[PDB]
Image: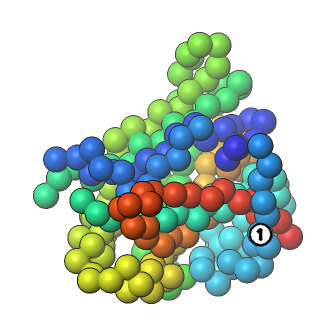
Amino acid sequence: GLGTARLQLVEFSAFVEPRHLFVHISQPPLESVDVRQIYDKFPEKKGGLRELYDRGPPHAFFLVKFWADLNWGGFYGVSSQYESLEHMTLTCSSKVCSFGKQVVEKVETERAQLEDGRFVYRLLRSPMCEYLVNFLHKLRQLPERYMMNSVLENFTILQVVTNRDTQELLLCTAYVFEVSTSERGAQHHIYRLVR
Ligand SMILES: CCCCCCCCCCCCCC(=O)O
Protein backbone atom coordinates (compact mmCIF):
# COMPACT_ATOMS: atom_id res chain seq x y z
CA GLY A 1 0.00 0.00 0.00
CA LEU A 2 0.68 3.71 -0.22
CA GLY A 3 0.82 4.18 3.54
CA THR A 4 2.52 4.13 6.90
CA ALA A 5 1.28 2.72 10.26
CA ARG A 6 -0.01 6.21 11.13
CA LEU A 7 -1.76 7.12 7.81
CA GLN A 8 -2.83 5.10 4.78
CA LEU A 9 -4.06 6.37 1.40
CA VAL A 10 -7.34 4.60 0.68
CA GLU A 11 -8.44 6.24 -2.60
CA PHE A 12 -7.32 8.93 -5.00
CA SER A 13 -8.98 10.04 -8.21
CA ALA A 14 -8.86 13.03 -10.57
CA PHE A 15 -11.87 13.42 -12.82
CA VAL A 16 -14.34 15.23 -14.98
CA GLU A 17 -18.05 14.89 -14.93
CA PRO A 18 -20.46 16.89 -17.11
CA ARG A 19 -17.72 10.76 -14.57
CA HIS A 20 -14.37 10.23 -16.44
CA LEU A 21 -11.24 9.41 -14.44
CA PHE A 22 -7.85 10.67 -15.58
CA VAL A 23 -6.17 8.75 -12.80
CA HIS A 24 -7.43 6.48 -10.05
CA ILE A 25 -5.93 4.64 -7.11
CA SER A 26 -8.22 2.28 -5.13
CA GLN A 27 -7.01 0.56 -1.94
CA PRO A 28 1.82 -7.88 -1.70
CA PRO A 29 5.49 -6.37 -2.14
CA LEU A 30 6.60 -2.81 -3.20
CA GLU A 31 9.62 -1.93 -5.46
CA SER A 32 12.10 0.94 -4.76
CA VAL A 33 13.73 4.03 -6.38
CA ASP A 34 16.64 6.31 -5.45
CA VAL A 35 15.22 9.80 -4.66
CA ARG A 36 18.58 10.95 -6.06
CA GLN A 37 17.11 10.12 -9.51
CA ILE A 38 14.18 12.54 -9.18
CA TYR A 39 15.60 15.61 -7.32
CA ASP A 40 15.85 17.52 -10.64
CA LYS A 41 12.02 17.15 -11.22
CA PHE A 42 11.15 19.25 -8.08
CA PRO A 43 12.36 22.56 -6.63
CA GLU A 44 15.61 22.76 -4.68
CA LYS A 45 14.27 25.67 -2.61
CA LYS A 46 12.66 24.97 0.76
CA GLY A 47 9.92 22.43 0.04
CA GLY A 48 12.52 20.73 -2.12
CA LEU A 49 12.49 16.98 -2.16
CA ARG A 50 16.13 16.69 -0.97
CA GLU A 51 15.37 18.90 2.03
CA LEU A 52 12.14 17.07 2.94
CA TYR A 53 13.87 13.70 2.66
CA ASP A 54 16.63 14.81 5.14
CA ARG A 55 15.27 13.76 8.60
CA GLY A 56 12.14 12.72 6.79
CA PRO A 57 11.49 10.13 7.98
CA PRO A 58 12.49 7.90 4.95
CA HIS A 59 9.59 5.34 5.12
CA ALA A 60 7.01 8.13 4.62
CA PHE A 61 8.16 8.89 1.01
CA PHE A 62 6.57 7.25 -2.08
CA LEU A 63 6.62 7.66 -5.87
CA VAL A 64 3.57 7.06 -8.06
CA LYS A 65 3.91 6.82 -11.81
CA PHE A 66 0.59 7.49 -13.60
CA TRP A 67 -0.37 6.46 -17.16
CA ALA A 68 -3.32 8.79 -17.54
CA ASP A 69 -6.45 8.60 -19.63
CA LEU A 70 -7.11 11.81 -21.65
CA ASN A 71 -9.75 10.18 -23.90
CA TRP A 72 -13.02 11.91 -23.04
CA GLY A 73 -16.77 22.80 -19.91
CA GLY A 74 -17.39 20.21 -17.13
CA PHE A 75 -16.63 19.87 -13.42
CA TYR A 76 -12.92 19.14 -12.81
CA GLY A 77 -12.29 17.56 -9.45
CA VAL A 78 -9.87 15.77 -7.20
CA SER A 79 -11.13 13.39 -4.45
CA SER A 80 -8.80 11.83 -1.88
CA GLN A 81 -9.50 9.70 1.19
CA TYR A 82 -7.09 8.73 3.90
CA GLU A 83 -7.42 6.74 7.05
CA SER A 84 -5.72 6.13 10.44
CA LEU A 85 -6.14 4.67 13.95
CA GLU A 86 -5.16 7.94 15.67
CA HIS A 87 -7.44 11.02 15.77
CA MET A 88 -5.61 13.76 13.87
CA THR A 89 -6.06 16.91 11.87
CA LEU A 90 -4.23 16.87 8.49
CA THR A 91 -2.51 19.61 6.47
CA CYS A 92 -2.41 18.44 2.79
CA SER A 93 -0.04 20.42 0.53
CA SER A 94 -0.11 19.73 -3.24
CA LYS A 95 2.63 21.40 -5.31
CA VAL A 96 2.39 21.33 -9.07
CA CYS A 97 5.74 21.69 -10.80
CA SER A 98 6.70 22.58 -14.38
CA PHE A 99 10.39 22.22 -15.38
CA GLY A 100 11.22 21.90 -11.66
CA LYS A 101 9.60 25.25 -10.76
CA GLN A 102 6.62 25.33 -8.49
CA VAL A 103 3.74 26.94 -10.30
CA VAL A 104 0.91 25.92 -7.97
CA GLU A 105 0.62 25.29 -4.24
CA LYS A 106 -2.77 24.16 -2.92
CA VAL A 107 -3.06 23.83 0.88
CA GLU A 108 -6.08 22.09 2.53
CA THR A 109 -7.14 20.91 5.96
CA GLU A 110 -9.22 17.93 7.11
CA ARG A 111 -10.17 16.81 10.60
CA ALA A 112 -10.57 13.10 11.41
CA GLN A 113 -14.09 11.69 11.30
CA LEU A 114 -14.97 8.47 13.23
CA GLU A 115 -16.25 5.59 11.06
CA ASP A 116 -16.35 1.76 11.51
CA GLY A 117 -13.74 1.75 14.29
CA ARG A 118 -11.11 3.91 12.54
CA PHE A 119 -10.55 7.54 11.47
CA VAL A 120 -11.22 8.65 7.88
CA TYR A 121 -10.10 11.92 6.24
CA ARG A 122 -12.27 12.79 3.20
CA LEU A 123 -11.08 15.56 0.83
CA LEU A 124 -13.79 15.03 -1.75
CA ARG A 125 -14.54 16.92 -4.97
CA SER A 126 -11.97 19.59 -4.34
CA PRO A 127 -12.11 21.67 -7.56
CA MET A 128 -9.02 21.22 -9.73
CA CYS A 129 -7.11 24.50 -10.12
CA GLU A 130 -7.50 26.46 -13.29
CA TYR A 131 -3.88 25.96 -14.34
CA LEU A 132 -4.42 22.19 -14.51
CA VAL A 133 -7.82 22.51 -16.17
CA ASN A 134 -6.38 24.65 -19.04
CA PHE A 135 -3.29 22.50 -19.19
CA LEU A 136 -5.50 19.38 -19.56
CA HIS A 137 -7.57 21.05 -22.32
CA LYS A 138 -4.44 21.89 -24.24
CA LEU A 139 -2.88 18.49 -23.63
CA ARG A 140 -5.82 16.53 -24.97
CA GLN A 141 -5.82 18.37 -28.32
CA LEU A 142 -2.32 17.04 -29.10
CA PRO A 143 -2.48 14.66 -32.07
CA GLU A 144 -0.10 12.00 -30.76
CA ARG A 145 0.44 10.22 -27.48
CA TYR A 146 4.24 10.53 -27.82
CA MET A 147 3.81 14.34 -27.94
CA MET A 148 1.67 14.26 -24.75
CA ASN A 149 4.44 12.24 -23.09
CA SER A 150 7.09 14.64 -24.22
CA VAL A 151 5.18 17.51 -22.70
CA LEU A 152 4.53 15.45 -19.53
CA GLU A 153 8.19 14.60 -18.88
CA ASN A 154 8.41 18.19 -17.51
CA PHE A 155 5.37 18.01 -15.23
CA THR A 156 5.24 16.70 -11.65
CA ILE A 157 3.21 16.86 -8.45
CA LEU A 158 4.53 16.70 -4.84
CA GLN A 159 1.96 15.96 -2.14
CA VAL A 160 2.91 16.41 1.55
CA VAL A 161 0.58 15.37 4.38
CA THR A 162 1.53 16.50 7.87
CA ASN A 163 -0.01 16.27 11.28
CA ARG A 164 -1.29 19.82 11.64
CA ASP A 165 -0.92 19.98 15.44
CA THR A 166 2.57 18.37 15.80
CA GLN A 167 3.81 19.45 12.33
CA GLU A 168 5.15 15.89 11.69
CA LEU A 169 5.34 14.59 8.12
CA LEU A 170 3.04 11.63 7.68
CA LEU A 171 3.17 11.20 3.89
CA CYS A 172 5.05 12.57 0.94
CA THR A 173 4.23 11.37 -2.55
CA ALA A 174 6.00 12.38 -5.79
CA TYR A 175 3.82 11.93 -8.91
CA VAL A 176 5.09 11.56 -12.52
CA PHE A 177 3.00 11.20 -15.64
CA GLU A 178 2.61 9.65 -19.12
CA VAL A 179 -0.65 8.92 -20.91
CA SER A 180 -2.26 5.57 -21.71
CA THR A 181 -4.35 4.44 -24.63
CA SER A 182 -8.11 4.28 -23.92
CA GLU A 183 -7.91 0.57 -24.74
CA ARG A 184 -5.44 -0.02 -21.86
CA GLY A 185 -7.09 2.54 -19.52
CA ALA A 186 -5.55 4.32 -16.52
CA GLN A 187 -2.66 2.63 -14.68
CA HIS A 188 -0.28 3.35 -11.83
CA HIS A 189 2.75 1.84 -10.17
CA ILE A 190 3.59 2.80 -6.56
CA TYR A 191 7.22 2.67 -5.59
CA ARG A 192 9.07 3.58 -2.37
CA LEU A 193 11.73 6.17 -2.21
CA VAL A 194 15.12 5.23 -0.66
CA ARG A 195 18.61 6.75 -0.28
C1 LIG B 1 -2.10 14.14 -17.00
C2 LIG B 1 -2.40 14.79 -15.67
C3 LIG B 1 -3.72 14.35 -15.09
C4 LIG B 1 -4.21 15.27 -13.98
C5 LIG B 1 -4.35 14.61 -12.66
C6 LIG B 1 -4.30 15.56 -11.47
C7 LIG B 1 -3.34 15.08 -10.39
C8 LIG B 1 -3.71 15.49 -9.00
C9 LIG B 1 -3.97 16.98 -8.82
C10 LIG B 1 -3.07 17.65 -7.79
C11 LIG B 1 -3.76 18.03 -6.52
C12 LIG B 1 -4.85 19.06 -6.64
C13 LIG B 1 -4.56 20.19 -7.59
C14 LIG B 1 -5.62 21.24 -7.55
O1 LIG B 1 -6.68 21.07 -7.00
O2 LIG B 1 -5.30 22.33 -8.18
**Residue 169 position within the rendered picture, expressed as x and y whole percent measured from the top left:** 71, 50
- Residue at 66 percent of width and 56 percent of height: 190
Q: Residue 34 sits in which quadrant?
A: bottom right
The N terminus: image quadrant: top right
Q: Which residue is mark 1?
A: 33
Question: Residue 109, can we see it?
Answer: no
- Residue at 53 percent of width and 32 percent of height: 121
Give above or below for 124 relative to 145: above
Mark 1: amino acid: Val
**Residue 140 position within the rendered picture, expressed as x and y whole percent measured from the top left:** 27, 73
Q: What is the crowding at mark 1: few (fewer than 14 residues within 10 Å), some, or many (at least 20)? A: some
Question: Residue 184, can we see it?
Answer: yes
Residue with the most extreme left position = 73
Q: Is residue 36 left or right of residue 195?
A: left
The C terminus: image quadrant: bottom right
**Residue 168 position within the rendered picture, expressed as x and y whole percent measured from the top left:** 73, 47
Query: Foreground: 31 or 91?
Result: 31
- Residue at 42 percent of width and 75 percent of height: 103
- Residue at 13 percent of width and 58 percent of height: 73
Residue with the most extreme front position = 183
Color theme of the render: rainbow
Give above or below for 58 relative to 136: above
